[PDB]
Figure 1 (spheres, rainbow over the protein chains, first blue to last red):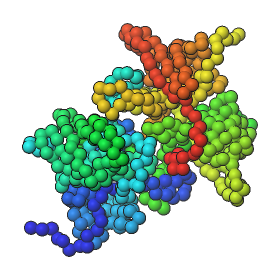
Figure 2 (figure 1 turned 90 degrees about the vertical axis):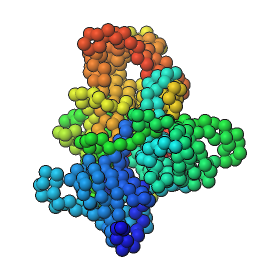
Figure 3 (figure 1 turned 45 degrees about the horizontal axis):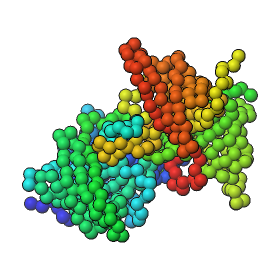
Figure 4 (figure 1 turned 30 degrees about the vertical axis):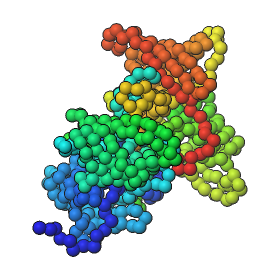
Length: 142
Length: 136
Length: 136
Length: 142
């Protein structure tokens, strides 16, 4: 049997880099800058989150499968997530907005923590599609 | 062939010593090879504080117990491999470290290169604990 | 004036948030200001995996309880300050964080800039323990 | 009173970056690459060693005063050294060679560890003088 196909496919597949907002000044909102975490949304329906640790072994922090649900939401069927352990063996529904600039905004809701405490919190994330630049930088530290 | 567990995320490594003229010890670096279940390969390199970059992609397929092919579509690190097959010999240890070798005869301009390439890659895994101080 | 403990090694900081339109929390970055006892100032920036670079130098002198001058010889980040004095207002907290402000009117080509600069710096210290996994 | 001035002054003063040797291949010696540690040899006779920790607070690992002794040796009079605690409140004599290419080789001998165990080991280090490049890189992450 087939999961529901009744959505307009979005360009979810890709390697995505987590971003954050950086300001030089205390009380002023920051501008978008890339960070150290990647989400691989594979062409064959698998999801992996992993984080670099400079000079050390990178680590997977979550993995599973994913499935688009509606024109602007998809689920991650998480097997294990060490960043967010209350999501283990559960579905997380992510609402998304993908811009032609390669920036994807995600948000998801979590009701309870692992100890059953009320949380009722929306999480918000900004991701940027990783691409191939025109030129191989001559001094790249591989 | 006996199917090897190639599919996964791999981190490039190098060897470091504090002194010259001695072998170094293995240390992870900034480049990743994503080998998907459906036979896609992507190499990308993190650049601290900047956008990561894809440096090659295509498809791949295991051929024998110690070799696989990358059918490269585009590779900006190794552009003589564009629309070519590269055959890689591989050995994967029980410690999750994979040693690759491959040979390239010519550069894109037809100059003789006749170079053997060696790469060490380590399988990226999920540790038991999320580190308290992690910079995501 | 009451002499402030300016002499030392200072690390530039910035503010980070996971979401837009909110204030971020303080995080250290890659640039250092070395304020020597003999009144020399050097700014340099680490570039991961590459050679660090000096981006400015000169001399400095405390003027009042909350200001000091940098007499810049050369600054490739801020080249309108070459052979000029920059007056910085400073406040150093009990947590070792120093807040700097300064104002620059013109760029090197004479274009009006009239910009206030804010910098947050943190005093670099010696922790009680050398971390076991440190990458020197 | 004055410490001995009977040496030909060398160009020790500077900010120095610790280097190591990197190879892509297991059993082959590496080439010189810069690492994350700095030694400030000040114009006014003070020494500080410190190490970056990417995304985190940098740390001082040793400090004191220094004094050239001979044409190719100097001492670090170490107050505290958390990298090498057997050097606390002691002099360490470093033999050096400074190249016109800005590379300095250092070596020093340590007899005993902090617990009094025999060590009798020569340490060897390679350092590179930090300089001001021609151009401010446009995309520098400060």
